[PDB]
Amino acid sequence: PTLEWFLSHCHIHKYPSKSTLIHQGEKAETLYYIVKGSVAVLIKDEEGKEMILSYLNQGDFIGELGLFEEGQERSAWVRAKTACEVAEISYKKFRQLIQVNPDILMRLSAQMARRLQVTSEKVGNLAFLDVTGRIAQTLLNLAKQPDAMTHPDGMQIKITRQEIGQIVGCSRETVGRILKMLEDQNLISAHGKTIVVYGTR
DNA sequence: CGCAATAAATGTGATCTAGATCACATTTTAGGCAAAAAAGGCTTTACACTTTATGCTTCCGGCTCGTATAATCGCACCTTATGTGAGCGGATAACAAG
Ligand SMILES: Nc1ncnc2c1ncn2[C@@H]1O[C@@H]2COP(=O)(O)O[C@H]2[C@H]1O
Image 1: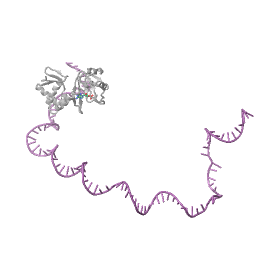
Image 2: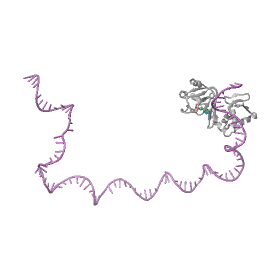
Image 3: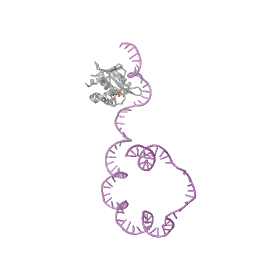
Image 4: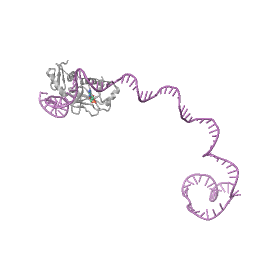
């Protein structure tokens, strides 16, 4: 449909792992779209602690905020998590496609609504719910993600002990303590990054 | 399955604050309602405006009249001296025709 009409003017260019698709400081002159794989977006402070806002899997767009208002810069950093195939379309030639077919814009701004609902309703849980409650909800949220692999016992995901604290809002030390505590009670499992939870499904 | 190497992620655990509890007595808070002090309200009376008829007076202003008067006339002295050519009508001399 409209999606196929979008790939007719794209520029196929594969990006290796640990690459740089979006550099905070450069000029936004290329729209990116995810075909296969996944990518992560995060920011940094003055020390070195990271902070992931939201994850973007396949079928999502990369850097679309610098399209509505011409003359902007890259907000956050976008590092390629895994081998992903991303297209390339200049914003200049994109604006001409909207004036002749606004329907194409109805697709991009359609995914910008869900990314706001999962963030606004998350703040409330990061002010009342304790560590046990915040992490508990996170386990189910990551299980609903398409990048999650089906497990005979439950769900198998791969996330570090830092990214967890960046979602529930806490220190990295606290995460490791509770994580190992649930292991003794036979509730979940962890072997570095891969965390297999139980009770799901 | 092990190997590569730049980035991100890992543990440590004693020290020292950061953030939270509770039930009851003290201290602050909010808008509430008249009173006082102020805004314009919309009265009714105190006075003050230039204006304009007038005519009477003195002072400054603006205009003429007639009168009185001599004249209807006479040297010697001081310092300069426009520029041209072009265009035009008129007066004069030389010429051919009758
Ligand atoms: N919380 C978020 N949810 C979804 N996408 C994001 C989030 N934060 C940053 N991004 C994307 O990261 C991109 C960084 O570059 P852009 O400003 O071009 O566009 C930004 C967004 O598209």
